[PDB]
Image (tube, rainbow over all chains, first blue to last red; front, side):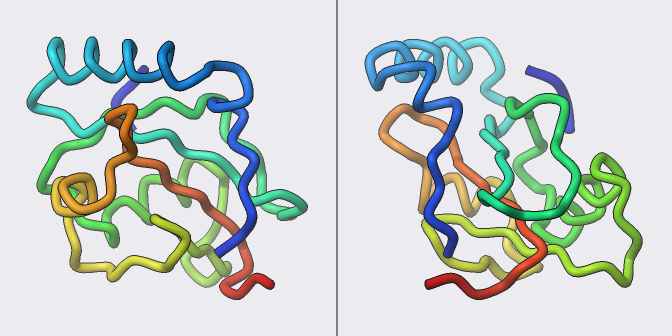
Amino acid sequence: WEEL
Amino acid sequence: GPHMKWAYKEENNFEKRRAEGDKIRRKYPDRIPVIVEKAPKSKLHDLDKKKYLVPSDLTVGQFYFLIRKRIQLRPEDALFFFVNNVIPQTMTTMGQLYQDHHEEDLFLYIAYSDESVYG
């Protein structure tokens, strides 16, 4: 998961 | 929309995905979790990852911008998104899309392609  | 065979779902069954969904909604409630994958056969560049977190107020239009950068596309190149197998409006926010279309595993799925219509 990572910030777009 | 395109007939998707989500790698995320091929790799993880519903129980495993819903467990992850519960965990993500618990740990990052201020973010919308999205699974992003490319339509089969699309010539567009692949994304390095498929799991993303986005602000609830981010619009589809702003989302298009972020994706275009990640797949090295120019403003004039064709790019279409499909949610719930249909194309969303640019003014809709990610939070609104999630509220109406999140999967039962608690994730919002978004497919991208260079083509707008599929049989």
